[PDB]
Length: 401
Length: 204
Image (cartoon, each protein chain N blue to C red):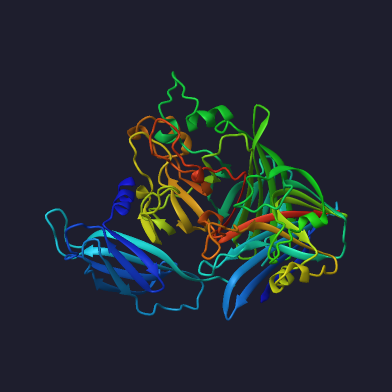
């Protein structure tokens, strides 16, 4: 995936948007743009609204102003996105016809958007029912432990907070089981107990509102007496079957910054494809996502796993506003990865060929995710602005059918 | 102009929950949407959760917070936060986190040309009269409204209004200063995230 990032950062055309005017600057030193046309497209939440093509005629180190025709003023809600791509119409010795050599995306105008579930309480769980949908929250764990559509269970593993990732080579550095490197991210995480932290239930309560049921939970993650993380959640299940999850996390200032702040569950279903409105199509992370474009992407599940020979956290897509998998839809503003391999398996397997697809599908939905680094892979390389150091984090999801 | 989208109340087991949603609009465009929850529990504490959406295409707002005019005028302001002096997100390195206690007058900086002033950042507790606010916020507290400051050319023309204006911000824009004839607020101090969340607890 990184290659695409390189391609984007090294591209020979730079773009600047001013109103509806695109300034295309050539970083070629010698050649005129004699085999380039600029395709542009305006889209609303992934739906195209207008497009066009303009031949590039820009001298080396020169500028070309391209005036866009009046773009649409869709009175519907959502964010307009302008995407430009430079296409080489004719083949070269090194490229086929239609080769994409450069691209850029900007946000245009945004228009902001302007039966009651029955609760049954037992000593062991809260059960919420609405039509053929059923949610089961375990009161001893404090987590959404099962979901039914009709009679079919949807979860193999409860929906739980996740603050760790299968370490990247950049997280490990030169640290080895025999020769620990204490400044490596993985060693700091392990020493702080991030991978061994035991969730402790502080609160689990249910309450029926006028048109919804509200489940409020609070957990503390602890290691050797120290509280690393506190998660306080609210689950609001309303008369439309939509489960709105609000998550507020506190992170101890003195514990190493966590790799991620999100949720994970093992979904019982395995679907052939993953659809999402977000950055894609390829794997992208907070400090490697410039090359990714915001759009409606639809890929086979296999393409959501990057087969790094040394397994690690992989396949994240950021800036995601909608995720569709099977009958499930998640909405919000999150990063996600979706695969057949748990973070645990990735972490404890040395070679990709030794991975075995687990039952169902592991979904990691993150409100926040740490950078991956890469300035070097033998010292901490994640820049401060990509570390999860804020101490308090908030994210909201909506899970529905 | 604030437009009410939602205002609903609901009694929980041990608290009352008021949920509201407002849209700020100008000439047909929605600039901001605020969605709040007020949870008043059996201890008298009012927990306020605020989630704000800001249109990507509107200029980044100077602040995202709350304001009210308190009826009381107290002699002193106590706070656990950055101080003792005025500090802003791009000017707070010199401020120290501590328990500070100053006369109310010292919470107003008398710039000859009136403007936003007196902000204290990184504040976890604020005590004024019988009121206590808790969370992680920036605040200023004075006898002068933002409107009066904006519409008055000289400090000597300011008149203390009835009571005390409290501005509690979850977020506040930088002040700049590289120059004062062009935009100087660096990107990392502009409120550009599009979505903001902050929580307060107001009690006696």
